[PDB]
Amino acid sequence: SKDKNRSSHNQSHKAHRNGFYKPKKSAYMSTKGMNVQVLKNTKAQRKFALAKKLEAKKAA
Amino acid sequence: PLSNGRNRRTRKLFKRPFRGHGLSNTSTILHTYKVGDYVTILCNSSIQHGLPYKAFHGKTGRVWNVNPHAIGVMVNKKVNNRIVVKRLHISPEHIKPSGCQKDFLERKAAVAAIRKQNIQLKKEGKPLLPLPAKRLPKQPRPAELIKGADIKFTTVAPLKFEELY
Amino acid sequence: GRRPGRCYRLVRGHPYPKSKYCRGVPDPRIKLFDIGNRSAPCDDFPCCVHIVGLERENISSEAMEAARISINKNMLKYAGKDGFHVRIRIHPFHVLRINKMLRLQTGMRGAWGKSYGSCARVKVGQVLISGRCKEQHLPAMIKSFRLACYKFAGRQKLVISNKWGFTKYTKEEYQQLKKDGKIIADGCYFKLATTKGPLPK
Amino acid sequence: CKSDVMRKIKIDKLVLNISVGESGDRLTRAAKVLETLTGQTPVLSEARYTVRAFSIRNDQIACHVTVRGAKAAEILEKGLKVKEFELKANNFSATGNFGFGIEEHIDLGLKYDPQVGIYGMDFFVVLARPGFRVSRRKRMQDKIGRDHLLTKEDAINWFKETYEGIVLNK
Amino acid sequence: GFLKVIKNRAYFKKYQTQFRRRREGKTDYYARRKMIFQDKDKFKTPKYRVVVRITNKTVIAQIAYSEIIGDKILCAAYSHELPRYGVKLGLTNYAAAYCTGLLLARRLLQKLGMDKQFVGVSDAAKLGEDYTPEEVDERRPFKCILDVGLARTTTGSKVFAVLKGMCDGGVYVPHSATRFAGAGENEEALRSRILGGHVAAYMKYLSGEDADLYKKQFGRFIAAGIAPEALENIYIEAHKKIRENPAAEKKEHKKYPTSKKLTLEQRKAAIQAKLAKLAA
RNA sequence: CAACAUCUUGUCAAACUAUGAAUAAACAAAGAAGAAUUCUCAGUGUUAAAUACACUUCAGGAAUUUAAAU
RNA sequence: GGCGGCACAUCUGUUACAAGAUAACGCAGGUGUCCAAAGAUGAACUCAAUGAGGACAGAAACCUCAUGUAGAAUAUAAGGG
RNA sequence: AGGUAGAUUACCUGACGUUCCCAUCUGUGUGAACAUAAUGGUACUGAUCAGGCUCUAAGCAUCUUUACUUCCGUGUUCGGAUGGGAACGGGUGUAUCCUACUUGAUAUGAACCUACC
């Protein structure tokens, strides 16, 4: 009882019904695995800006 | 029926250009890549270490991270019915600067040059120049008149068949 | 036991030449491809005719051999040994496969084919056989060419070229150029007078 | 002020080679005869291809050595007096070198010993001109010009002058 | 006859020429691209090399960083300008190689202005021992790689006499002191060879043996009246006079045109003239 | 003679190829949120040192123009 | 169906259609290993072949010059380098 | 004009010859030490007696090659579409895209930083 093995027939029509789901913008903004020193520089500035902001919020 | 090897079907894809073997340029390793740039992945079979997968050959991507010896590249891959984001790290021997925005960067400079003169013209009170017109598909040609003194006529008719033997 | 000619007539499949992968190919039946006075200079035989195939099909090496013999005997009969030079312009570079069926210990459709023979995949308008002669033997040359076509399949066409004996130049172009020295005989063909390279002394 | 001084032909290298198939004892003696003949230790050559006809790849077969300068000249004089300055015209290469081979060696026949044996050497002479270094230097290696390169007749004239030895055309 | 020349058009249609400078035998592109590769995360920050080349008569030394347009030379010091500092003869010695390297180190720091805080070693007593320029206050020294080219780096090579000079000049060139004139013996061997001691023993040796050999090898020294003992003191003053004025120095050239090309008219006219004279 | 060179000649390749389409593949044609400029400008680090350069919501802040870019 | 074979885990070229995917008990072959060096690095050198020479030595032994885009070698199948 | 470093990697290569060297470069002299190998041939070091002989660089040739241009030729092939013709085999018309080999004409390098002339 041999059977047909494989076909691509009707596979592109199926794929375009709910068509190619593009990724959102947040998919291109990931920073996991970036440069180690660049990450250190960015974190150092963010901690500096945040501390200044919270100090000012404490004064008022 | 092929085998599922990593570098299957690359007798012609991974061959070097005719009379283009040996070492590459020096511009390839001296070109400076910055984040946000557009690059093209081009596997160099001459360098087998870190060779990118053959499915990314010819794809255009964007630089997302610069590491001491490798340049991060982010391309788009197509899956069953969706698209995923692929993040690779490729040495400059396998990538190449992309010219995809070369024409766009020309219009940006032309507009910026015009806008730079407008702040001068508005400062001095003169009317300001307009920005360059937008690109349009080849438009229908207008009415034209052809002078009758520098015109020659060539008669066109079906050609009598002649045997090629 | 040779299969009917209708089994291997249509041009089917990729070309299958004899190479390091295809072994055990029977030798082609045809071995001579130039007949007549093959060494006659270019100016001896001005007349030229062709056999032009009008079908896309296989021509087996048996048909080429059966036709070369037919023209050779006929042209020796009518013109003589030195009166003609007929060249066959198709070679059997294709190998046909046969899957032979012999009890109940037979895999029925589970097998490939063995090398069977040779043929040339011709196309429409291709020149199959050509030949050259003088004016005094053209009628005997055309007659022997018609008889050869009975050894082939499909439909053939006899064409009389307006050129010289296997040269691309027409009858009057050859006369003018040769008298100008642009044409240099080489025993059986010519060579154009080159106007390039180092100057002589 | 003529530049003829920059085209003076001179000996630049002389090679003596003894190729005997056997390895051991005789080769050790065949190496010692070159040490006495020239003055410097030779280099033992290995078999490039194994051939059963010659009973020969890892094994030492030959032992060649090259001498240059004044030492090369005097050994050439000894190897040419055996031939009595008689070199055939067909002994000269197309590139300006010549060579020959001998069976007996004068060596030291006073205390000649059969244990050492009898060996035959071959003499090959490589001539040159001042300026031939451009093909041998490490940096900016180039090719010598055709007119600067020697030829068979160039070597013949040198031989018939510096040694007066006539050349046979037989 | 039998030729079988492998130079036909079939050979050339597939021939692939090497890089032009490698075709000249002047550049090792396999090692050049190792010294040329700046880290990608250092955008356009120059990487400096000491290009040391020694000809038959002069010791060239330059400081170059590479760019796509070509190589740019930050500074360069030659040995043919050593006569301005009191060294007339022997411009390619181990001593003159040291002076050339020292001059470049002082000349460069003057250009960048950092010569006050980086002085290196100066006394002749400490010529033989290794010295690596170090951090001053919190300012790092000028770092520069050594480029040797197709020169074999033996255990006494001159290209390490230039390198030793720069380090004593205050420029940091990474190195190991196992290829200097020492690496065997001690600082006295390096120091003596730096002062021309190896040179200033041959004439004392040669004079004892022969007078013609002495005259043939050191002919210009005899005319200039430079004794084998004055060599040591000459190089001491050259180092002293270098550290106080390394700032380089300031007509129209006389060209010599050579052949010039032939235009299409002259090129075509000759062929017709050659064809005419053959119209034998 | 052959043989080997060399200049022509006729016919070829799914597991030969210099060259190489048509159809195709993946980008760009203005989203840290619709541009641009000017002034001001900090934290880390690169750096010989930086006023260079990199990242930091084109760090951040304020003015002027501005809805244009098949 | 059985007997035969493994298309059952797996690699190369081709079928295969110049993106990716991609059939048959399609075609031509391959794997269950081998390596303290055949891993890492530094230096030097240039391979196969051909022409011309050199005692034995010959078409095949070893030496020298010249030409030599890899026509050699790189553990293995094939394809890449 | 020359030399060092290069980027483009034959318009830069290969063969036949030709032109200067005034500086520079090269070739050239020697082997004491560092260092070098069987060989001061290489590489290393010391030098300046001579030379444009080679290199290098510049130019020549109905030169091979290579790089642009036309032509080959809208010819090969190709996407879309018949109740189009043919027994097959294969080959139209329509609205479109359009190579290659070859041949002929031209060229035989452009350009960057430093020093010296």
Image: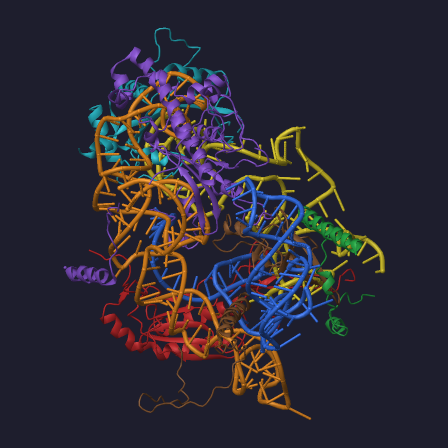
Chain colours: A green, B brown, C red, D cyan, E purple, F blue, G yellow, H orange
**x then y, percent, for residue B126:** 48, 77
- From what the image shows, is residue B97 above or below residue E113? below
Q: Quadrant of the N terminus of chain B?
A: bottom right
**Which one is nearer the viewer's eye here, C8 or H8?**
H8
- From what the image shows, is residue E197 above or below residue E12? above
Residue furthest to the top in view is D111
Describe residue H63's horizontal placement relative to residue E247 as left or right: left
**Which one is nearer the viewer's eye here, D84 or F64?**
F64
Describe residue B115's horizontal placement relative to residue G76 as left or right: left
Residue drawn where x is 58% and y is 62% of the image: C16
Residue furthest to the front in view is A60
**x then y, percent, for residue E144:** 51, 37
Q: Quadrant of the C terminus of chain B?
A: bottom left
**Which one is nearer the viewer's eye here, E239 or B104?**
E239
**Which one is nearer the viewer's eye here, E218 or D20?**
E218
- From what the image shows, is residue C9 above or below residue E164? below
**x then y, percent, for residue G34:** 68, 35
Residue B136 lies in quadrant: bottom right
Residue D38 visible in the displayed image: no
Residue E196 visible in the displayed image: yes
Residue E210 lies in quadrant: top left
**x then y, percent, for residue H91:** 53, 80
Describe residue C25's horizontal placement relative to residue A21 as left or right: left
The mark tally for this picture is: 0
